[PDB]
Length: 14
Length: 115
Image: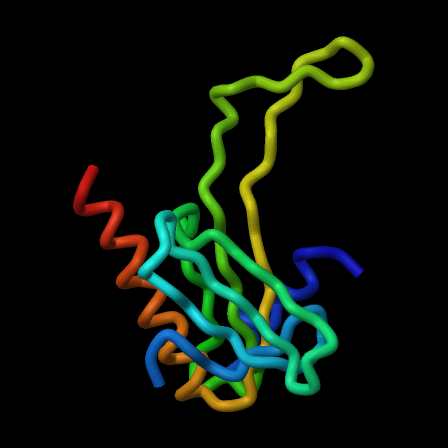
């Protein structure tokens, strides 16, 4: 819904 | 795999092609079917965002330079702090996106070295 949401895609999880 | 890489724009599919023959060099996205087309100025590209290979998350983000020093006034007669340009693209082959992120870096650095 927000830009930060798409940013998480780059952060992901190990 | 240089100056071209099948990229997805606005959730739509197409190919992303870069041309450094034009000043300032730009990038043009062309749908697969040819229903949508997009153009971006690379010379502004201040930062390149790309999802790691280890991350199943496929995506590529382009950051355009800004100029908040300009100080633009709003309809309310008050000054505002402009925001930096940022594009969002999606790829299916880490290699293709890898080329774009690599090729784009060559353009920025190309202008960075000059200044």
